[PDB]
Image: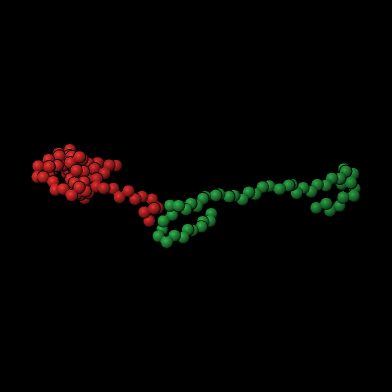
Chain colours: A green, B red
Amino acid sequence: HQFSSLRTPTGDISGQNKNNLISGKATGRVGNYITVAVEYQQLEEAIKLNQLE
Amino acid sequence: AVGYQLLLRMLSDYSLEPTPQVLSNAQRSYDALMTDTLVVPSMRRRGDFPVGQGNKYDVFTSDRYYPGDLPLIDGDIPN
């Protein structure tokens, strides 16, 4: 919060108006999936795929 | 009372001197009128005067001491 001050010659603030209390917030949200997917046939892994790790 | 007072106040217009009987009657009427509208004030307590233990004072009430003339200055306007 932030405030502002008055200025009077004798401390009298009857006529003037006081400060308000406005509350604000910051909102965060979740994003999207980061997905990586691969696929291969059975025979590809049977013969071709070497050192898959 | 009113008539005698105004008569005494307007006699000088005709340059005539009032008689003692008229003065006495005016004084009597004025005294009666002043007696009618008479009030005698009563001196209330000072304000710091303690209230005796026999009155059974209590908290949440200002009965501990006699209520004087309240300042009637509260809030920001006093200062």
Q: Whole-percent x and y of residue B67?
A: 24, 45
Task: Name the residue at 68% across, 47% down.
Answer: A30
Please state if A49 lies on the left or on the right of B2 as rendered.
right
Q: Whole-percent x and y of residue B34?
A: 17, 41
Q: Whole-percent x and y of residue A40?
A: 86, 45
Q: Quadrant of the C terminus of chain B?
A: bottom left
Q: Nearer the viewer, residue A21 or A14?
A: A14
Q: Is residue B24 visible?
A: no
Image height of A49 relative to B31, above or below: below
Image height of B28 relative to B79, above or below: above
Q: Is residue A53 visible?
A: yes
Q: Nearer the viewer, residue B34 or B53?
A: B34
Q: Quadrant of the N terminus of chain B?
A: top left
Q: Quadrant of residue B28?
A: top left
Task: Name the residue at 24% across, 47% down.
Answer: B68
Residue occupying the far left of the picture: B20
